[PDB]
Image (cartoon, rainbow, N blue to C red; front, side):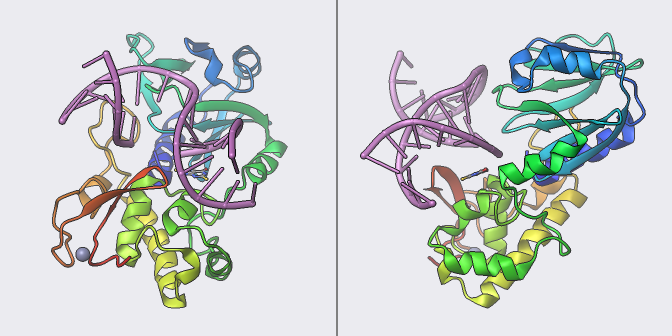
Length: 271
DNA sequence: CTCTTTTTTCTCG
DNA sequence: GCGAGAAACAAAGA
Ligand SMILES: O=c1[nH]c(=S)[nH]c2[nH]c(=S)[nH]c12
Ligand SMILES: [Zn+2]
């Protein structure tokens, strides 16, 4: 998932599990708890969920007075809220059991991670990850964004994917944002003129906020949180190889950029 | 059978 | 420091 999908999961968890006492925690894949599963089980059993936050693509469970469980879903992580008798599924790894259901974390590729840290370690934790600003008008300052672009010879798509200019874009939304802003993904950022940077800045905010509003992009679903999204019906380029661009009618092309599949309109996004 | 495809962090030169 | 490539892992498609 990308930021909009994580925000959608965050919102459903906030509505459904805040106030719930963790009755027990179990793992079939304890090694994905980077701070130690047995330690986490000892610390969090019996505590109540107070809130769910997010920073970039990271989910943050606020548990008890002092605990923060930082969860990253990476490529394929999925949470679901299940009955206590729900059958095990093959790629389920962890579960937090409440009195009237359980929150199960599943992840085919096993990339996702859990880290238990304290409240006052959250801000230093994200500083150490070098996460950039949230993609909002209030936090995403165009002036710094522009100065960083002007200094760099990096290509715009890999630089945006670093999470350092702005947090939350992944392969789907960076391709959508670049199409919307009419920027070729291989453009060196120091070649972007001010008006292109302005359009890019606004487009990042607008695309991600639209995606949040539509509940993220779910291709297929299953019973998982976040699976009722509608943003996939709005994608203009991602996964549209060979289809016609909706602005100019040229076929969308797919290339590889810094090892990522990359979809763009060659007319609208001039090299 | 092989090769390729689908977020973060590392090695290597 | 950089970029290229690959690793972590599993599955599906050519
Ligand atoms: O954290 C990241 N750092 C880099 S350098 N590239 C990249 N691409 C995605 S998606 N996430 C990240
Ligand atoms: Zn076009």
